[PDB]
Image (cartoon, rainbow, N blue to C red):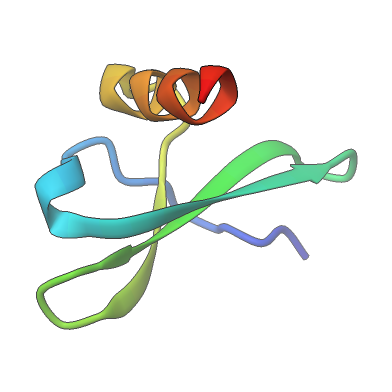
Length: 61
């Protein structure tokens, strides 16, 4: 079973509280994020540009 089933491409950082990185060689790279509004658990597509910027600001810092 993969940590994420469907990925959302219409999510923005303002609606996410934190991003979780998962390196699963059974499903490849997947990222899980929670909606700040209802604090739900949703899966975000690792192809969004703001996601890459978040990883870039967390890796250099």
